[PDB]
Image (cartoon, rainbow, N blue to C red):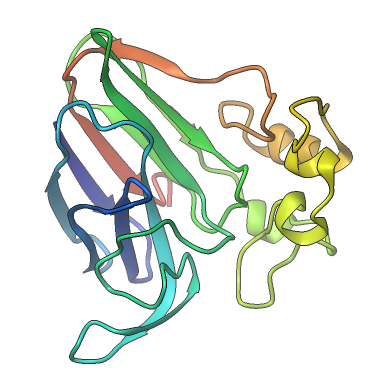
Length: 207
């Protein structure tokens, strides 16, 4: 499948693409304001993510740090990123269908539109000023709005027993972005698309 990754933000981001235990395509790349990156993700990829990273520094090796979404210090991500990260999530060619969502389960750093570029389904968006509106106890000094699990490490926010409900902190995310996962048992906002559809991830879709 092809994913086009567009930075419409006024600031540079370093895009990242991983399935947890490896890189998708080149794994990451700098995207300047307006600049785009074309990746190929293997059919059948299950549990893939794409995200933006902010305020990064990388040496000539491709080693360094990011204030949000840092993936073990590497330009070319092999692993998931450090919260806070807004997440484009997907599983492709799962019994004939592709499944996509946006999630705030791991917090929010950048607004995002995750749209199929082929027919048969609809896109999702999380485009609110979540960082501007972020409750004080979830503000990430590095930048961004951490979710509550990251911050408090409770069974309730982390859904460690598989039994949790919504919380004041999850409802904040949900009110700013009803089309994105706010906590693990949230009513699913997943999008069933055709198998082998194609996609565009846009950072800062409105601005």
